Image (cartoon, rainbow, N blue to C red; front, side):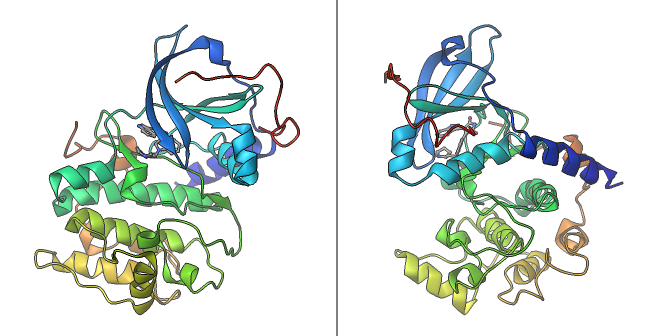
Amino acid sequence: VKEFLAKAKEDFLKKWENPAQNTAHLDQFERIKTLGTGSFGRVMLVKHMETGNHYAMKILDKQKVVKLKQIEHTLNEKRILQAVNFPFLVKLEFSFKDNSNLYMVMEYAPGGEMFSHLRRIGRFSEPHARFYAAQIVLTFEYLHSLDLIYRDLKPENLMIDQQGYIKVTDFGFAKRVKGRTWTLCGTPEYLAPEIILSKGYNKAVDWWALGVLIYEMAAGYPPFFADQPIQIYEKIVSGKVRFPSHFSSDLKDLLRNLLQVDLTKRFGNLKNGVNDIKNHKWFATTDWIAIYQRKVEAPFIPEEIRVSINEKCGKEFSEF
Ligand SMILES: CN1CCC[C@H]1CCn1cc(C2=C(c3c[nH]c4ccccc34)C(=O)NC2=O)c2ccccc21
């Protein structure tokens, strides 16, 4: 049964108290190309020279992490990532550091990412949409089981691997909390209301987020949108949603129960909790273990690194 979860709460708690450090070195890798550069670090497709494989290497300038006051978000991302295992979570393969930089070597997810697929296709049929939502629910079941709130769900973070399945990436806003917490963070279209009204909030913000994701997937656009962020903030608070013509009925009611402004009458956060997600008419034709196992047919399958001679920021990244 869910002896699987307590077996994984153990595996994660052990890696959490004694995280792995220094499991590779930059010399044993080779620059192919710069995938991207930005908020989440500067990432590089690289090849492991003694094995053949490819990986996404995120490189962070330590001095710049300190300047931008991102020390603890960075240590925390790494610490969570090296402790978690689930088939829809991208894997921190290796991590290490050197004089100038930190390095997180990740599974390379080469099939592009969901934001970009919505953009170019237009929208997903409801079955296709439902294939992804399943993986996210099973992912949020796991993460929530180890007391990890995700807080960055959005299409841009959801890569599509070579068997059509989803890998969640970016743990930058992830937090380990048993109780409640308060940081205003995350993509505005995806924020649940209690985050904006600056009360505390809990695990439940990830299910609101799921609903925003389900909507955006199914519809082609997110349910609360504007040219300005406070205008997105304003709509979420007012809780008024217009489903487009072609939405099915059973779905249109799923999105009323995940996008519920009222904490206690909201799916995910209940007596039952997660099973209200699974035991529901829109997920009737969804085998919840064939998804885990990867047996379902997926609906669609597509600079110099200057390193200083002197060590920088030694004490502030000693845990890394
Ligand atoms: C910057 N955005 C454009 C593409 C996706 C998005 C960033 C989301 N994202 C994708 C990451 C990963 C990968 C990326 C694949 N193509 C990219 C292009 C830019 C940035 C990252 C990636 C990857 O292969 N494995 C990953 O884990 C990643 C690693 C750490 C933090 C955020 C990340």
